[PDB]
Length: 52
Length: 49
Image 1 (cartoon, helix red, strand yellow):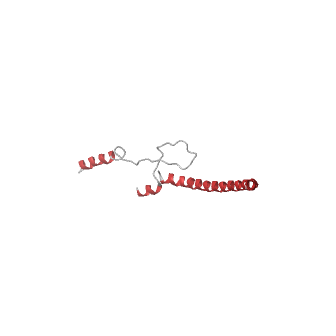
Image 2: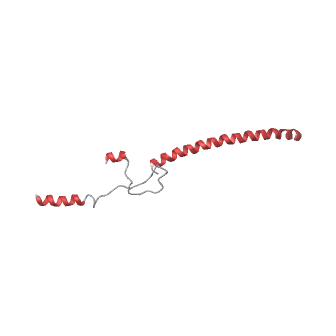
Image 3: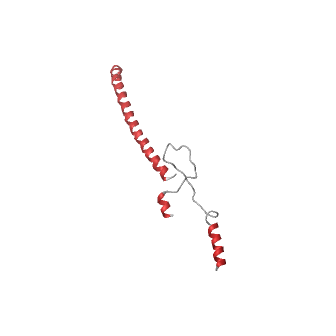
């Protein structure tokens, strides 16, 4: 049992940041002032975030 | 296109349609000026008749 629990833990931790799969990142910004966009501060809409 | 993007242009596109209506009003005003010109053209038309 301990051996299974160790192996499963490595898969879970691996499966978080290292093997994660994420969103498309389509970008549209309302403020006209924003002339340059960081492209990493893009987040999903609040309605979609609740479902996720 | 993104629906937020579409919503923003439709605000602007509706604004453009309003501008087109204003332009149609301007064209009608131009037609009225043309009609005043046509009334002076009317003396020449009487001479032509």
